[PDB]
Image (spheres, rainbow, N blue to C red):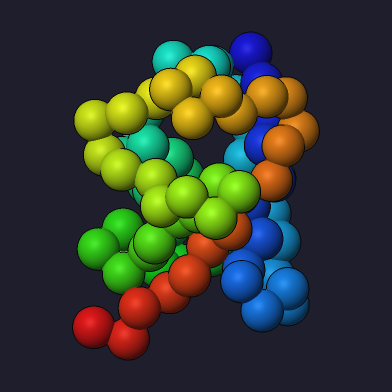
Length: 77
């Protein structure tokens, strides 16, 4: 069980996502992020240490650890 921070690329908005496991899928993270930031998954692009995060992969795949941060960019289209 784990928690991570999601912060916008501009720095202005941040939310903890919790009740995750290291096996959580990126697509599932996108859905959690929608509830908190109100951004449809299709417009979310997620970055971990500058690397774009892809569906089908887990947090463990990206080596994300407890309370690490991932960036959210919101596309216009």
